Length: 169
Length: 169
Image 1 (cartoon, rainbow over the protein chains, first blue to last red):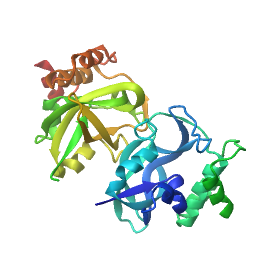
Image 2: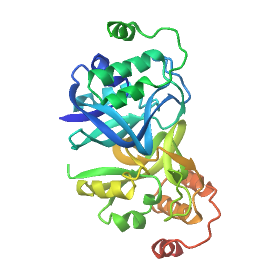
Image 3: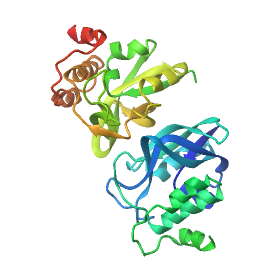
Image 4: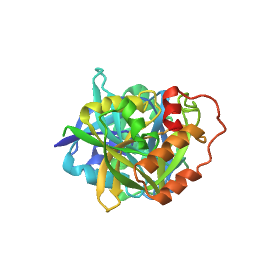
């Protein structure tokens, strides 16, 4: 009746995931070996929520991606796929094996883009990701990596819920 | 439940091929994957030394379709099948897809695609295996025409005795 979800993007932040998934429960922090983080425009299309490149991952030996594993009820599978834009070709559903800091291997559902053009994230998107990583105690080494991501030059506004989250941050 | 369904779109379209490492695989049905495009390539820039040409992959592309065979397999074969796809070497990633049978029924299947590759044409031998499986397993004749239309590379050397034998007959 449950599944595990590996979040590496804006769903790193508790308040963000709980927006559409209030019953999501923190499971653990984990590392996905031999994948690299990237930001981009699915189908060449710019996120009208984020106004910049959005998070994705691809296989790349020697690289790693840290994220948060969330536990979720199986009844939320369709909703979570909807959120990720599966039917509209935005992300594909994946299965990955991630490692906890104690070396336990965890099988999780996640998402990645299959057809995108690489593009820098907006300041607000980067900030939510930065806040999530910090909140959930991802390695300091990884946190600084996220801090050093070059954002695009968007100086406009995102949704009030998101903007309010950053203000409280 | 004991079993899972696996969607094959490459060399595992051929019964004799999939049976060589997965002898207990059973034909379930033919199905269509909507809004995906078939491609061939060198995963992580490496050319397959089994096939000596680009190997099969898929990516999200509105408008396009990929037809394939759904195989029913015991859940004890999961790790083996992941092993065959080179998941651990970063060749393919495990995906979940929803496919439609010719009668319009949606099926949830395990499959694979490449996340980091260079586009390169298949070897004549690879194309033959795929064409054979497509034909043997009753994929629509228009899709068979698409497959027959694939431009192969120029490889005319030796592939394994097991593969050459299958094509021969």
